[PDB]
Image (cartoon, rainbow over the protein chains, first blue to last red):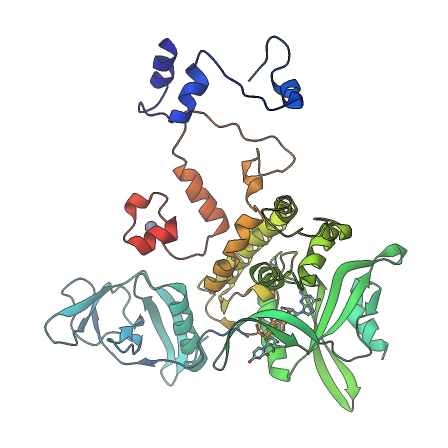
Length: 50
Length: 113
Length: 308
Ligand SMILES: Nc1nc2c(ncn2[C@@H]2O[C@H](COP(=O)(O)OP(=O)(O)NP(=O)(O)O)[C@@H](O)[C@H]2O)c(=O)[nH]1
Ligand SMILES: [Zn+2]
């Protein structure tokens, strides 16, 4: 994609940690919720922030 | 009660010099303790200002052990010599407990000011 | 008698109350780190030669502050007086007071240490390294004195277990700032000792839980600027307590202040080598073995263990 190229051209050597590649470039997110209180704290409404 | 050195150590002389082959003869005061597998020498001492390479003959007579030094520290002591100005020399890499033992025995028995 | 208490109180004006009977000592069972020509170890011995007075706050409430005055021959008196006069400007040194009193047809010298804590660092280390749930009164008292928990917390038995009740970690992590302040004061004390020209061994039982130092009885003198503190067993015996209490937590805040937000790092950053060297310089300045932040540069597997 073009986001991967961006964050790789923002590195000082071309090396980045792998754990941040899905965090800043993935287009789809999946959330697994055990009970109602956790649903009310995380994925409330139609849009949320994370 | 935690003490620096119960039971003291011994010392005999050795040779020293400025650079690698500058060793002439006895120019130092090299403290030591006898480990069963060869005796480890602890602390040198100089009337000269800048020595950097001392040398000790081997227990086998084939090779010779070299000892390069760190920058000295100056002090003057009293004895029938009157003012006795010197420079202590610890073999570079000597850790803190060994310097503690050396200074302990030295300042405890040898006069200082 | 009672002139003894008034002489002990001195210029402090502290309203002391006895912890013993008269001008007699008080026997306690305490942990010591000992090495001499006869015995050695890290064990609990019987401390005898000390008179203790507890300081009283206003409203007549007892606070955690004690005056410990012990009794000396005439040589250790002068030795300690000389060393203390050399070291009295450090903020990490407890306040001492030297005087002479009359017990009998004798004038006897006394040394008083002002505003100490009931326990030392050795007591905490021993309690956490020799745990036994059948008798743990020292640990309980330390936990309730410094507001880590309350006295009824010890009724939810299995309270010490790590698997059952994993909430004890939150209780233990309330001592981290005390431990961190103790480390900083130790570094200050080492710097002062080096600048004054004093050579000695640092043990855990000569520091209270506020961080102050005392007992300069095995120290000697050299030329100023050439002192040597020996700190090999202090740090090593204290090491297992630094991660149990999470002492370095305040290092993740904006200016090492627990009442400020977390530092926000760059996501693309992975190196952190200068940070490791800064941390080592701040907390372990006089540990005199080489530290490699990256173990590719280590010399053998012993060095690998040391640096990891
Ligand atoms: N901090 C503190 N320590 C106390 C108190 N009452 C007794 N002590 C004991 O007194 C010890 C310090 O006394 P001191 O004899 O001067 O030090 P030391 O560690 O025994 N070494 P040394 O025997 O060479 O003097 C502490 O380690 C502790 O075991 C108190 O109220 N506070
Ligand atoms: Zn290493």
